[PDB]
Image 1 (cartoon, rainbow over the protein chains, first blue to last red):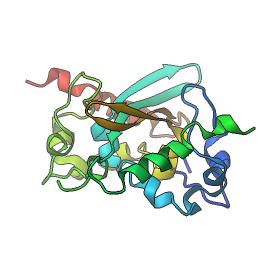
Image 2: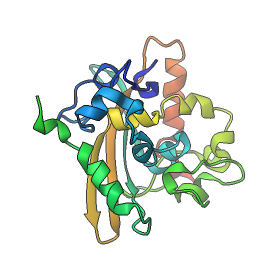
Image 3: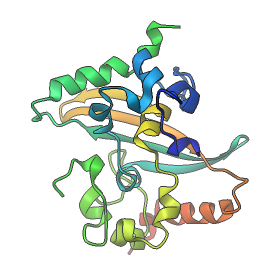
Length: 108
Length: 110
């Protein structure tokens, strides 16, 4: 599948599908070791995926651009998704997301 | 309209402006869509050819740079990334035309 359509699982994990996590621009930085190994099989995946955009919202919310560079033509995207401060589960949603953001710094 | 913004689906009955706000230049606004796509959402005739570039939830969290920013307004999950087009796809030149028709299209609206 094209990269953007891949679904990571235990059989095809986040590193396999999307590369090692790291700090570089355009390199993914999200996932602790458990999520990296399990992808969508991770047992708290639904609580992560509630923040992922639909295809319509991806194109509706984001700033989209196109860059032609020596490596190819790239669709660029930026945006932000607001957590619901009134959701009783808000504090747990913050904990969960923070557990994965830049987790790779703490392990080889 | 009751869905969280990120889960909304624009259609001809719930257009891109209704679901995602007016197109514009500001960092917080979306910039994508000509008048036809804005009115039709996922009912647009060439929506599949655009949606082929949108990430799965796994790819969104796998490919993007994700951040958490706390501001007066709220707590925001930020995202940025880049998706490479396949220039060996026979449809590539059509894809470029299509994307170019929608990116910052709002600048030429009446």
